[PDB]
Picture (tube, rainbow over the protein chains, first blue to last red):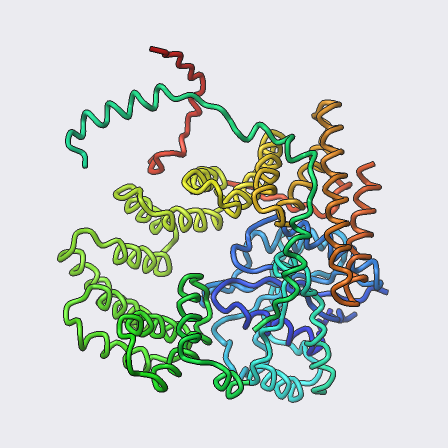
Amino acid sequence: PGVKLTTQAYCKMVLHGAKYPHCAVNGLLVAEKQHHTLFVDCIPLFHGTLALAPMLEVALTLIDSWCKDHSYVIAGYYQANERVKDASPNQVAEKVASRIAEGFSDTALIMVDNTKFTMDCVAPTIHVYEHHENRWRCRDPHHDYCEDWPEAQRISASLLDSRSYETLVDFDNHLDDIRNDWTNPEINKAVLHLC
Amino acid sequence: MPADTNKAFKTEWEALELTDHQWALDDVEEELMAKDLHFEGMFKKELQTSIF
Amino acid sequence: AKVSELYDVTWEEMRDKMRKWREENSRNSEQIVEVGEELINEYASKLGDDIWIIYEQVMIAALDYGRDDLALFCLQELRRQFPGSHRVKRLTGMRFEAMERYDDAIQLYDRILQEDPTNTAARKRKIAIRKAQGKNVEAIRELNEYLEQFVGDQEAWHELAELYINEHDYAKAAFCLEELMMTNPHNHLYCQQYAEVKYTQGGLENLELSRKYFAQALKLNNRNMRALFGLYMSASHIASNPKASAKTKKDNMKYASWAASQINRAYQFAGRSKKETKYSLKAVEDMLETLQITQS
Amino acid sequence: GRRFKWAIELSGPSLYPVGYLDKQVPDTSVQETD
């Protein structure tokens, strides 16, 4: 089963990682339920301590309420480590992956690397882990998960060059300040306009 | 200024034995029946500031 | 916006903003260095005492951001006036650690300890060197050693709690947060973190303890919605468990229903701000209705 | 329980801390009034 994702979600993930480069970041990809797995968009969950179930329950239940409003389904959950020389999945990541795999039959664990994380990204710089309820832990050697690569580079370079990524909002900022949303409307407008 | 460390140690040892325990947290019912209007309070005044 | 921002400011406001940033100890190295080097080339006249702290802050930010040239530029200026100063030695050791050859930084810290026996900063930096060099267990042991030798620093307690969070040790982090809350009882943030830590532990008695701790800090600030959400789910979980009494479960349902109404009012008062807030109000409304039906 | 659906369960696998104590040692009762 191939894994395909739109440039919008990848830009969201990279941008959320850029927002907090000193702490670990967390995100949740969303697909469409109706063999290849297509990802629609991602939402950033939390940042910082990143070892708490209480707020995770709130966030995941809110996302579930969201997915039953516009007829969506939670695809998978992605996590980046704090240390640069760290590319191994933590226990919380596997627990969340199993929790999402109970419902959906296709949950990929996305790992953002840190060693190949610069302004001029080469290309893939994503680790796709394929986890289950059993002891199956395999990561794909190298495949193509993005649709158009040169256009993706142009938009990513424009987004990272121009300092317009301070507006990205997380679920924690929603609790701290109700006013900011969490769908990132301006980011969607920019991804549509740049194309 | 611990002039006599041992004597101060003993004095604090007996002072900590004298003091009792009264959990001031056990009274949570006062907040139970109340009103929440201050969170409406600066929420009005938290709109007015934008993001730099 | 860069030229526009640089136009509608004065050096006084910029210095005051930098002082406020120092007070709030935020992580904005990009903006700190952006306003740091700008006032070093525009004014560069007076406020020596302030500009020394500014030099140290700017170099600290540059060590984080991308620029060792300005770091060394400020290092020479700091060394020019005070030839023997242990703070500059610590800063140089931190930059050396950032670059390469951690062992010479360790040797510099050892010499600093040899000169001044009471140097908490050097020991903390060594503890951080072994946090990232080796495993976190040895760093935990050394942090405990320094904390035992002092038992003075709250930052050490919070760092120990943070390091114990990654090891899934809520028993020791419980004591850490209890001690850190005892000194500061008016800070509801530590109470909220302690309530979350106790909730993650599990158990009906721990659930009740976390619920009461959530409700205590809920009246000190009276706005934090994380604590109110945690209290509502604690009440719901108490209701879920079969091991409960009738009247306790009853009052727990009242607590949850009251928190639900407070959520509804909080989200309805945000609906007049924008025009997209009605949809989020709807979303939380379906969430609360589903949870209410499931509880009832 | 299935009622809560999303419920993440977190488990936990020389006595240096002075405070964290292995033995609970309850049963303290002091009554001194002079």
